[PDB]
Image (cartoon, coloured by chain):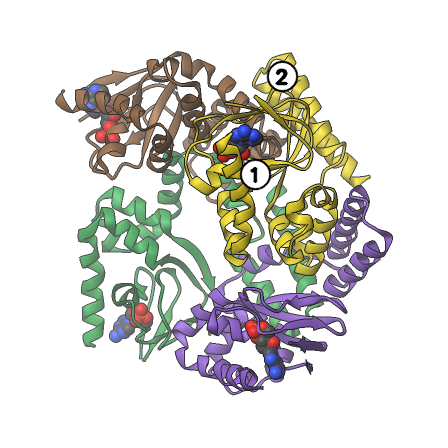
Chain colours: A green, B purple, C brown, D yellow
Amino acid sequence: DSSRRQYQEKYKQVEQYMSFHKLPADFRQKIHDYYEHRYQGKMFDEDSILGELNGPLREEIVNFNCRKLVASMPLFANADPNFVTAMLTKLKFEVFQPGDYIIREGTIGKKMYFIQHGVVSVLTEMKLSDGSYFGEICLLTRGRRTASVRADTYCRLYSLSVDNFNEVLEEYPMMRRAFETVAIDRLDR
Amino acid sequence: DSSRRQYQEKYKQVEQYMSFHKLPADFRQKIHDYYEHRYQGKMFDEDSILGELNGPLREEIVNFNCRKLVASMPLFANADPNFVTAMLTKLKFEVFQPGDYIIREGTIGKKMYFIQHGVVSVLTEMKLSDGSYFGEICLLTRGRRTASVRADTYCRLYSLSVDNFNEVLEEYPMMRRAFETVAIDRLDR
Amino acid sequence: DSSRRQYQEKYKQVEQYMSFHKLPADFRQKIHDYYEHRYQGKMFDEDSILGELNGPLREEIVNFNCRKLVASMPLFANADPNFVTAMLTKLKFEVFQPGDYIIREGTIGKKMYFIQHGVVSVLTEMKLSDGSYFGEICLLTRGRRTASVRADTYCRLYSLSVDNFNEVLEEYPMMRRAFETVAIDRLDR
Amino acid sequence: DSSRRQYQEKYKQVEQYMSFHKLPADFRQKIHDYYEHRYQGKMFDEDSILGELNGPLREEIVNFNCRKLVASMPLFANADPNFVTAMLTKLKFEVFQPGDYIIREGTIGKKMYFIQHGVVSVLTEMKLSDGSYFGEICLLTRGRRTASVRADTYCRLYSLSVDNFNEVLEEYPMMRRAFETVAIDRLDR
Ligand SMILES: Nc1ncnc2c1ncn2[C@@H]1O[C@@H]2COP(=O)(O)O[C@H]2[C@H]1O
Ligand SMILES: Nc1ncnc2c1ncn2[C@@H]1O[C@@H]2COP(=O)(O)O[C@H]2[C@H]1O
Ligand SMILES: Nc1ncnc2c1ncn2[C@@H]1O[C@@H]2COP(=O)(O)O[C@H]2[C@H]1O
Ligand SMILES: Nc1ncnc2c1ncn2[C@@H]1O[C@@H]2COP(=O)(O)O[C@H]2[C@H]1O
């Protein structure tokens, strides 16, 4: 239960930090809920652990932890396993809370998001859920966000930066077509 | 009180460090006073805490912690909330002590400062206080400091590097005019 | 036995991490075996220790820890001691398990491997063991891997990135010929 | 005595590390002596401590800790205090042991050394001591070391990288002449 204790002590610091800065009670509970949803009572120095392993072990772990995500998207499901692994390795797990603005219209976009679980509202009005992704337009155009995207419910997502996006596509150039298709179709709508 | 203990133990190391290097008694008290003013008896690995959160949570925290600063300046008060947030996110909190040279005339300037609280003396003689900023000239010209700026009283400031300054303005180009106006007006004087 | 305890507590976290993510029992034992083979019951913040030393001490340590490796290869054995040291300093120790894909054919190669102990199978069928190296072709061509290389037995290797490879050769340009010879000979086969 | 304990526990790890890698008894005592000379029974996360301070405090500390060094050289003694501070801030304290090769002839030089205390032998035969510096030729030519420099006695030095060297001179261009004079005079000899 060393991981449980790590979470408890770390959360104690967070609580004291919020108290020190006199954050409102409502925000403190929002923080409380975020930690439960995001870490679920346990914490590990993930970077330290994966860093002690080797490439093969790290790739098997990410492929397993993302099995759900992978199964939910034709993008990864029907692709070269090596492509999927390269992509998955670059993903960053993120949890957003109801009402959170994940993307704001008109700003410079430098990341896209893959939905593991949750519902988002795209407003320029439409919704996207499990197995869908968004924010790909700006990674392709390098322009400004074409719409705002807010979390409707709690959202468990994986983000990918434009730099990592292009890095992976350097090795798998033809996979860019998948994102472009989705981008074009949405730009038309 | 884990944060209180962190401060106490950390300060113990500092004291032992100053003793090891035989720093004068007067400087040791200056160090003592600095820690009280800067951390106020508590310490947190701020980077670790904010890093465990998400973008929305981090932005709400910085906007709240800087509410005072924001209210004191037409620059931020009357601007696009997204601009203010982008700027605030790049700021670095710093505390200076009476007599400290924040900026020395003739040197290459790579940062500007926003005054949360305190009084500074600009010498090439004038003073600046709460709600004012300085050091913007060099971020705009990339030249040498046009004057020295010393802390008159204890000063609670937020600094912004030229690189972060230009990064934010890449997204909000027109806000550069605000800094230029102040710069031009002061260059004339 | 502070190092033994470090290993035990660290492994406890790993085990809890694997449990948290519900990894299969078989993979958990694979992880168990990896840690035994790689760290052998002890762990040290190697980077912190070597960083407290100086250049001379670090170089003597790496030359000693790699004495076995050096003796097993004409490349290093008959070369300028300064070259060997520069190279050794850039190496990264890695342990692979039976069946592990060290290199996959057709992918972009950015590293080569020197075999301290173990047997690998090169498949485009041949094997390489103690004292041999592989993955040098892509560091020279900057192209795609000409074959896959799987660990046949447990493998104790030292990897070298293309960037560190070229950095060392900036100081020892003529040593590139050794790698080219091996590359040409294998490309012919 | 938290700093004393830090040293004791850290040294315990070092000793266990050397034992794990089966380093010879003679080298283990060399390591033992190095730690005593370099840290003197105490250790602090220097980077963490100085990082908690501000620019003014850090500059006063470095100027004080290097008071001895500064007094021993016309270079710094008769220069602009701001130049001295900028330089001192970039220095890295290093301890070398008798017989250590600080610089090897013919290699690419990327750093120079200022002697706080100790004696070095320059061999292409001459010696340099307290208040003198060496390794400046390569920082100026970007070529290969014109000679080897070995520690004759224990040496307490401060090194400066070519990059930091040129960075400081960007602000103080005319100080480069001081190093060139010494370089030219030695190249003639
Ligand atoms: N009509 C749409 N249907 C679904 N998603 C959309 C639609 N329009 C825009 N989006 C998504 O909203 C995202 C906003 O940021 P981007 O412009 O980078 O990428 C956009 C698309 O991923
Ligand atoms: N006349 C003035 N009134 C107020 N502030 C000034 C005046 N002159 C210079 N300053 C400030 O002092 C700063 C010194 O560094 P900079 O030249 O970067 O920017 C300068 C201005 O921000
Ligand atoms: N015929 C061969 N005999 C031994 N090794 C080979 C042979 N062919 C390829 N290899 C090695 O397998 C490696 C696969 O990655 P690279 O192409 O970078 O470099 C290749 C060589 O190092
Ligand atoms: N004749 C000399 N007298 C004193 N120092 C020297 C002499 N010749 C070379 N050196 C120093 O030895 C250093 C070796 O590395 P560098 O060539 O970078 O710079 C050299 C000088 O700093």
Task: Kindly indicate the quadrant of the structure image that contains residue C119.
Answer: top left
Secondary structure of the residue carrying numbered label 1: helix
Q: Are marks 2 and 1 on the same chain?
A: no
Q: Nearer the viewer, residue A149 or C64?
A: C64
Q: Chain of mark 1?
A: C
Q: Nearer the viewer, residue A166 or B186?
A: B186
Q: Nearer the viewer, mark 2 or mark 1?
A: 2
Q: Say if B116 sits above or below D23 in the image.
A: below
- Amino acid found under the numbered disc labelled 2: Phe
| Left or right of D70, for residue B61 | left
Is the CB of the residue bearing disc 2 within 8 angstroms of ligand 4?
A: no
Q: Say if C72 sits above or below B48 in the image.
A: above
Secondary structure of the residue carrying numbered label 2: helix
Q: Where residue D107 sits: x, y (%)? A: 44, 29
Name the outermost residue toward the left: C188
Q: Are marks 2 and 1 in contact (CB under 8 Å)?
A: no
Q: Residue at x 52, y 33 (%)?
A: D186
Q: Residues within 10 Å of mark 1 (few under 14, many from 20)?
A: many
| Left or right of D108, for residue B144 | right
The picture quadrant for ligand 3 comes to: top left
**Mark seen at residue D27:** 2
Q: Where residue C73 sits: x, y (%)? A: 35, 14
| Left or right of A31, for residue D57 | right
Quarter the N terminus of chain A occupies: top right
Question: Real-space Cα distance between discs 2 and 1?
Answer: 34 Å
Quickly name the residue at label 1: C13
Q: Residue at x 46, y 74 (%)?
A: A99
